[PDB]
Image (tube, coloured by chain):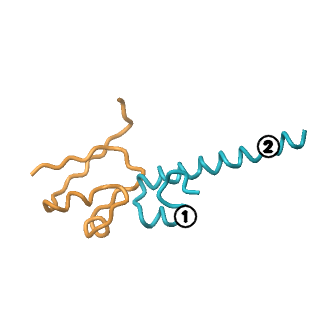
Chain colours: A cyan, B orange
Amino acid sequence: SKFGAISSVLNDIFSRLDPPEAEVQIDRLITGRLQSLQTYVTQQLIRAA
Amino acid sequence: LCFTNVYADSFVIRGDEVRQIAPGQTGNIADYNYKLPDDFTGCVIAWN
């Protein structure tokens, strides 16, 4: 999932973009994936209960 | 603000070459004369 960024591949962000906003794109992707993993863990906790 | 120590770098370049002085920006001056690190904090001054 692109999560609002321009690419779903980190190396694409590296090559096709210069660092200063490549950092912004990486931050967006990282926070999106962290949210996904948080959601998975929360649902696992409820199901475990 | 109050800084620890300030380093001033002075030189002269061409008119269109001014864009090359930037973090993560490549070019003849950048690759062979003067390259700014990406984690660069500071001002750059250019006047004709």
Sequence-first disc among 1 and 2: 1
Q: Mark 2: which secondary structure?
A: helix
Where residue B21 appears, as percent x and y from the top left, is 27, 57
Q: Chain of mark 2?
A: A
Residue under the image location 24 percent in, 58 percent down? B19
List the single residue furthest toward the top: B1
Q: Give the residue pinned by disc 1.
A: A9
Question: What number is the disc on residue A31?
Answer: none
Task: Check disc 1 and give the amino acid type.
Answer: Val
Q: Residues within 10 Å of mark 2 (few under 14, many from 20)?
A: few
Please report, as a chain letter, where disc 1 is located: A
Which tag is nearer the camera, tag 1 or tag 2?
A: 2
Left of A29 or right of it: where is B18?
left
Q: Which residue matches tag 2?
A: A43
Q: Quadrant of residue B14?
A: bottom left
Q: Nearer the viewer, residue B7 or A41?
A: A41
Image position of A41 with respect to B29: above or below:
above
